[PDB]
Amino acid sequence: HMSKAFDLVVIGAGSGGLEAGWNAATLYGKRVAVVDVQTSHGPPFYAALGGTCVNVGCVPKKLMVTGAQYMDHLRESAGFGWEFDGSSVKANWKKLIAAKNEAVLDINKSYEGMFNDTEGLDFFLGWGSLESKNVVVVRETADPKSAVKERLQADHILLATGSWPQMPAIPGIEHCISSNEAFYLPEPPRRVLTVGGGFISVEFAGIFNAYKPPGGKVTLCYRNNLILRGFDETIREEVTKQLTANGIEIMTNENPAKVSLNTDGSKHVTFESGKTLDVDVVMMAIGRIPRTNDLQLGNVGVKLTPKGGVQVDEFSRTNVPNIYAIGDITDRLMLTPVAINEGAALVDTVFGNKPRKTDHTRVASAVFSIPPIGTCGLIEEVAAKEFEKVAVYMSSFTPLMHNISGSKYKKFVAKIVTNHSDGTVLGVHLLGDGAPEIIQAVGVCLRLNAKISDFYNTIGVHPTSAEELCSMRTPSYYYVKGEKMEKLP
Amino acid sequence: SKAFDLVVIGAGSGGLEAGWNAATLYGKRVAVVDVQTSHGPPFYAALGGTCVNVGCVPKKLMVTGAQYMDHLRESAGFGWEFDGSSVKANWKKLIAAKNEAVLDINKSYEGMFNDTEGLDFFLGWGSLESKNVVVVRETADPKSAVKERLQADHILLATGSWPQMPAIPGIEHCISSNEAFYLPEPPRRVLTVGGGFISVEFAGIFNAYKPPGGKVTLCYRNNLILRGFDETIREEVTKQLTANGIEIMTNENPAKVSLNTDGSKHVTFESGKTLDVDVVMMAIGRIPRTNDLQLGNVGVKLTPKGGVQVDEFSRTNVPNIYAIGDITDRLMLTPVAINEGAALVDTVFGNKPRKTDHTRVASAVFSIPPIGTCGLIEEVAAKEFEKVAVYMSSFTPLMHNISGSKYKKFVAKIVTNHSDGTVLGVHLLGDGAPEIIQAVGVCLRLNAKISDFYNTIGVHPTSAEELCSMRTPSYYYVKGEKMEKLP
Ligand SMILES: Cc1cc2nc3c(=O)[nH]c(=O)nc-3n(C[C@H](O)[C@H](O)[C@H](O)COP(=O)(O)OP(=O)(O)OC[C@H]3O[C@@H](n4cnc5c(N)ncnc54)[C@H](O)[C@@H]3O)c2cc1C
Ligand SMILES: Cc1cc2nc3c(=O)[nH]c(=O)nc-3n(C[C@H](O)[C@H](O)[C@H](O)COP(=O)(O)OP(=O)(O)OC[C@H]3O[C@@H](n4cnc5c(N)ncnc54)[C@H](O)[C@@H]3O)c2cc1C
Ligand SMILES: Cc1ccc(OCC(=O)N2CC[NH+](C)CC2)cc1
Ligand SMILES: [Br-]
Ligand SMILES: [Br-]
Ligand SMILES: [Br-]
Ligand SMILES: [Br-]
């Protein structure tokens, strides 16, 4: 049996890796090989052909958040005159998971068919690692002593293996799960603790809250004082309130020290403070770390950062000339559309004679909390470190429809941060229904260097939440050489 | 008799913007006239204007109410279970909640007048007596009792529009959208007459709140509803309204309406077809509201179509008299009227002439599912530009394959000047289209090119990210002719 030769070998058939591979083969006529560990979603390896987003990430979680939103819809409908037997209402978690699984498997199968069909784009099943500068080895398991299925010769090698959940080293860690397992829980937990202040802990707290059985309770804990570090502070505070208002308990300044099993099999959590909580599921969502261990990068000398990601330059090049890395393995912005952009840029540069580097600034993104967040650009405290004068335009109010729905706690927040010296929009931050959809074209505006006057001169669409962004002419407050103040001196 | 810098006739979207800005920003003395202090019969519009009282604000609440018909059904695909036979839509509760919300806004504007220096409200019917005198009477009759005589350096006409009713026998047995907002019971069988956004939006409302055995029929006299919107989207929204149980009668137009013994209406179409309904709602158009103003007393010129004639700065032919909003019979939208009012006051009372830009105005239809659009449709573009590209994306979102509403295709279209890639128009149909489109209007004021959209990184998963994923034209117009490939 002979080894096979390729222009490009991609390790990991995920968001970034599939983009690079498809583009190299169909746009530039190159011969591409792509490696992944599993052909469809779920245990044992969870991620598979398609990547983390498709299998156990953005795509299934968005379907599940959509299902959870119906708890709010059924209740809010009464304000508009809808009547039905409230006592008959039930959230069938097994139906939700079965529908999600079928949707994901359909994507798996379509990717499989693309590889069966496409000239110069071949898929290989197994664990990829680096043997030498131009040879990728595919083995039966992550163990480098397992059996060799293929050796793939490669002029260019792309590392795109993504990331993996981080688990803290506490006694009883084996009694806990990550988001990987949460996507497959046979029944919805009556009592659940989600550990983390980031978007995965927050999104899953919303999902469990809607599908919990009658006696249930969702608790989210976070070791620092305020969840969702990195997001707008006003939005961090408001989303805490609105999660609380929908019945989720938020323990800040709290962190599990150990977990043990009660005699009935439930989980007994002891926090560092000495507080205790009994739950049926503990889901760790304290971070995600780049997947480098199995690549045997020592074989060729690819340098990692102190933090643990593959080091790259602006063009995704490692320190070995023909080996590149994109996506979560670079441990920067862990977002599917960033990985895709990096992949397309790398291939245009290497095979297309059109050099291009990904712009990591002013990237629009979202949190599918209930209600959701949409953001693009700098938060005000970051901007105030870089610009002498920063203005903040802010609108926050309960929309009229939620005075009828009864969910009066649902304040819509719109904030615009500027460089006041010339009006350039530095960031936009949104909380409320529709915020992920509103923010997308805001990203185009920021890439065009929009100023606040470009927003204000635009005529609103009425009635919308989005029109608040085009009705703000006077700053609410300022930062002058880093100091917050209602007025310029 | 009383003396003012500015008298505004009509306390509406445009009128209140102009009055409040003139008083608070420029310290002027301002009087504002309207015929009613809160919403509803007999004059329907009131303090706040058409949008506030019988327009955008109440209709959006009612469309939101109607969407729950879809949400309740669609929840089953995501595992929600409940007794479907127990579901009912209480129209009276909807109307009561809507009434309370509107009345709250009415009261708020009252307090605004009480709290603001130089801003006075006068109740009654205003008309032009002389070039610098506005009269306020008890009724629309120009011979009813005078209540006030207000002299003004400047007069602003801002009385809005009114529903157009065709001259057919039995027109008096039909209603308009004014009365639709106050029907005691939801009509079981209703015909909405017209192809425009008001007919289409109310059709969706009645469709959700109709009693058992109900049916909503929309008729329109030409071949395809929603003239002036993107043609792909006109065809799709037709298809998706039909999938939700609404009957679309095209190429049909009422010829007469007559009363039945049971109180329902017998409609005879020009074609000879007949239909018995409980309610006939005419929504064929809205015309400028000029007849009670006595414009002949001063000679304000009208256009052939009936709007007050204005230049780009909202000035009539009579010095010191201005017209903004629906009375100018241009774009009939609340944010356009507001923009016009503000530009006018900045021009007259500040040192800064400003004129409203009527191109590239974003707007929406709250049909189910809704439309959001900004800028030019492709067949208008193809008459102004030698080479036009159309980028098109149309699919059913994954969530509606699970929800069971598989007919709900999302549509996104971008229209460009292909010679330089300048985005001329963007057109959207699907959940969230009105929210998605707002920042697109800002893009068009930065002379965004198609490559500016495509080079922006998407937010995933959203419908909106479709706008940043289109590289290759679907087809073109060259010298006005549609073709799949360039020559
Ligand atoms: C719960 C959750 C929700 C998320 N939600 C969002 C969201 O809403 N929006 C968003 O933009 N992002 C979201 N993300 C992030 C998104 O999933 C990632 O940023 C993106 O998938 C990373 O793309 P990538 O190409 O780096 O790798 P991935 O998509 O992770 O693909 C890497 C692939 O490599 C395979 N692999 C690993 N090691 C090997 C090996 N040795 N040999 C062969 N194959 C290997 C893996 O099986 C996997 O398929 C979410 C992530 C999670 C975990
Ligand atoms: C059903 C419906 C739905 C709509 N939905 C939308 C939407 O979603 N978005 C949107 O942008 N637009 C919408 N519109 C349009 C919007 O309502 C109008 O464009 C806007 O209200 C016009 O503002 P204006 O300043 O011209 O006058 P208006 O807001 O109409 O105010 C005119 C006022 O003048 C008063 N008046 C009239 N004659 C006299 C007189 N002789 N003396 C004293 N007072 C007088 C009236 O009582 C009224 O209050 C909708 C309209 C309707 C009918
Ligand atoms: C289980 C369920 C879900 C949604 C529902 O909305 C009402 C509906 O379906 N209508 C169509 C028929 N009309 C005569 C009345 C309005 C009703 C039941
Ligand atoms: Br269940
Ligand atoms: Br401005
Ligand atoms: Br018609
Ligand atoms: Br037509």
Image (spheres, coloured by chain):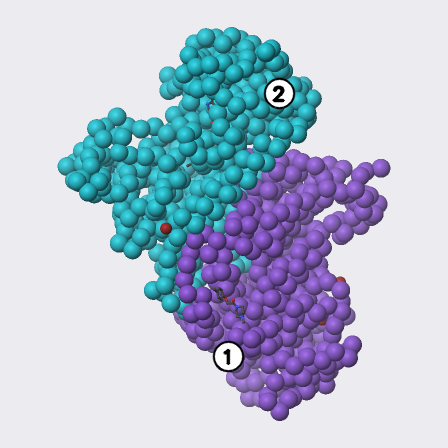
Chain colours: A cyan, B purple
Tell which tag, 2 or 1, sits nearer the viewer: 2
Q: Residues within 10 Å of mark 1 (few under 14, many from 20)?
A: few
Q: Does B199 sit left or right of B419 as displayed?
A: left
Badge 2 and badge 1 both on one subunit: no
Going by the picture, which residue comes out furthest to the bottom? B261
* Residue A11 coordinates in the image, percent (x, y): 52, 21
Along the line of sight, which residue is nearer the eye, A168 or B133? Answer: A168
**CA separation in Å, label 2 and label 1:** 66 Å
* Residue A216 coordinates in the image, percent (x, y): 27, 51
Q: Does B182 sit left or right of B317 as displayed?
A: left
Q: Amino acid at mark 2?
A: Val
Instruction: Determine which residue is flagged by label 2.
Output: A32
Q: Amino acid at mark 1?
A: Glu
Q: Is residue B6 visible?
A: no
Q: Secondary structure at mark 2?
A: strand
Confirm or reject: label 2 Cβ below 8 Å from ligand 1.
no
Q: Chain of mark 1?
A: B
Q: Chain of mark 2?
A: A
Q: Which mark is residue B185?
A: 1
Above or below, B152 against A211 in this view is below
Above or below, A248 against B149 in this view is above
At a point 75% along the width and 39% down the height, the residue shown is B418
Along the line of sight, which residue is nearer the eye, A304 or A163? Answer: A163
At a point 68% along the width and 44% down the height, the residue shown is B392
